Image 1: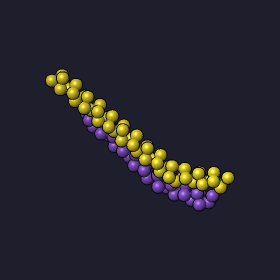
Image 2: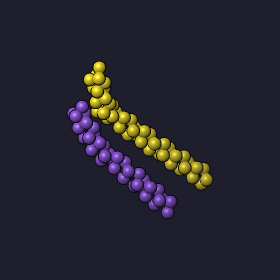
Image 3: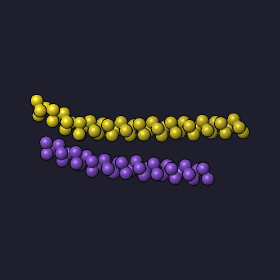
Image 4: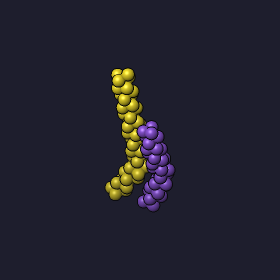
Length: 50
Length: 38
C-alpha cells in the first residue's frame, strides 16, 4: 500500500509535474493574449480620439 | 524511493532553465514597456 502511494508520488513528481508546467505555460499564453487585447483596446481608443 | 529522488532532482534541474527563461521574458517585457513609455 505504501509502495502504491510512493508510485503515485513518483507519478506526481514526473507526469503530473510536467502537466502542471504545461498548465503554467498555458496561463502565461492567456496572460499574453489578454495584454494583446488591452493593446488593441488602447489602439481603438486612439482611433476614437483621432 | 532513490529513483524518484533522482527524478525529482533532474526535474528541478530541467525546470530551472524554464524558470530562468520566464524571468528573462519578464525582464524583457519590462524593458519593452519602459521603451514604449519613452
